[PDB]
Amino acid sequence: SATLKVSDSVPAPSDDAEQLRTAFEEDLIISILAHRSAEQRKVIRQAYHETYGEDLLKTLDKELSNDFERAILLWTLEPGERDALLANEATKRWTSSNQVLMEVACTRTSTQLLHARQAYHARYKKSLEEDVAHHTTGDFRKLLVSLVTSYRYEGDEVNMTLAKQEAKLVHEKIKDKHYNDEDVIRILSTRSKAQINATFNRYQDDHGEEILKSLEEGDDDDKFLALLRSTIQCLTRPELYFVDVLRSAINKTGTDEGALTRIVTTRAEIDLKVIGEEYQRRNSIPLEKAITKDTRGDYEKMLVALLGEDDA
């Protein structure tokens, strides 16, 4: 699942901070942070702030910034505050094409999303809800708002009878092309992930083709269905959603800014290893090589080091 390679023996935080201070005044910054855990790094900032009276991030936290720097920020922030920045940039420059709101909302557990929601308050004196329903429009808004306000139950419980009925209902709607039906929304927003897969297992048993296959009839450029599609991979098999965000960007075709870094850093300590496995399959090339393709500066180097393969 996780690719991050942590030292089975880590030094003292004050010493990591000292070296980092010196490295900040590259291969050293990577040899440390790209091999520490969420806590060990936390302490670092903490012990770093004590020593020099100055947060190592208040300096790198900025819009116009170098990709290597960006990769230092997103990764060094606590996972909760690292999503708040994303749960905030997506709303500033939002477009019906920006699915980064569904991503953070559907690829996160219940607790992790509570941290993001309990971090959008602190750093923004606002809620993630009000801003989402503030800057988004139409059906995209009804979905993005519905998804970001969820606090799903995370158990195994499966109501097979409800699974078929709603699978039936969602099935009828996909037929008439009502990809924006209120019911499809309610289900994929309040049911346990055990209930979402079980429903689609019913949708695939009681029909034949995978849910995503059903979608193969929507309008030519329907930008909402695209949101649904991801909300089907992000909630079912995230790794199978991340590989497709990687393949694009790496090809330089995507319209998502920072998709590459926004994913490596976030999933490194989660399911990056699976994502990677599911990557080589779709590309016939190890992700580490796809990234170190044409360029290999400190930024591409940090990206790969977070993948484990520091020397790719």
Image: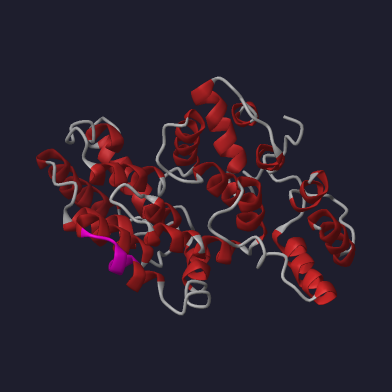
Residue 149 at x, y percent in the picture: 36, 68
Quadrant holding the N terminus: top right
Query: Up-down: is 51 above or below 167?
Result: below
Residue 117 at x, y percent in the picture: 46, 71
By secondary structure, the bulk of the magenta-drawn segment is best described as helix
Nearer-the-camera pick, 127 or 272: 127
Q: Quadrant of residue 37?
A: bottom right
Left or right of 242 in this view: 288: right
Query: Up-down: is 259 above or below 246?
Result: below
Nearer-the-camera pick, 254 or 129: 254
Q: Is residue 297 visible?
A: yes
Q: Is residue 154 visible?
A: no
Residue in the picture at 87% in, 57% down: 19
Left or right of 155 in this view: 60: right
Name of the residue lying farthest toward the left? 176
Left or right of 34 in this view: 194: left
Quadrant holding the C terminus: top right
Query: Up-down: is 84 above or below 282?
Result: below
Residue 99 at x, y percent in the picture: 36, 50
Residue 46 at x, y percent in the picture: 76, 72
State the extent of the magenta-drawn residues as a range: 132-137
Residue in the picture at 65% in, 60% down: 60
Tell me the colour scheme of the image: secondary structure
Nearer-the-camera pick, 258 or 287: 258
Residue 135 magenta: yes
Residue in the picture at 57% in, 45% down: 261
Residue in the picture at 37% in, 57% down: 93
Residue 153 magenta: no
